[PDB]
Image (cartoon, rainbow, N blue to C red):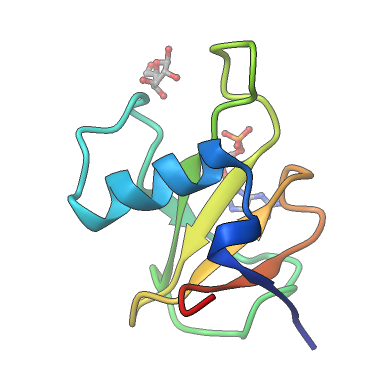
Amino acid sequence: ALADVCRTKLPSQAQDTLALIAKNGPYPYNRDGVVFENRESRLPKKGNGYYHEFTVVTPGSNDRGTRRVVTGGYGEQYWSPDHYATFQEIDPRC
Ligand SMILES: Nc1nc2c(ncn2[C@@H]2O[C@H](CO)[C@@H](OP(=O)(O)O)[C@H]2O)c(=O)[nH]1
Ligand SMILES: OC[C@H]1O[C@@H](O)[C@H](O)[C@@H](O)[C@@H]1O
């Protein structure tokens, strides 16, 4: 049961991250692209290595912070402002 968000409504940092995803980087962190395990199953329960996580920069700071995009195996994209506590499916069509 998944909240949905239009790509245009995403903070501009989140959109930068999707742009880096679409050209496969370079990414600003070695941790970008690591397997997201979906341990809590807030996202569709899928096989090993389906999901990958990518940093969204906090505005102001250049630390990683708590903002993230998880991608799925067919290019589904998920937004998390709250360090994997909740997810919204990104609709790239709006
Ligand atoms: N909550 C949660 N975090 C995960 C899961 N799988 C990987 N992570 C997080 O993804 C990141 C890379 O392994 C780590 O957090 P981080 O964003 O602080 O680096 C790790 O804690 C998961 O299934 N659930
Ligand atoms: O040790 C490797 C790590 O260095 C950190 O400073 C960065 O966030 C990443 O590039 C990586 O996850």
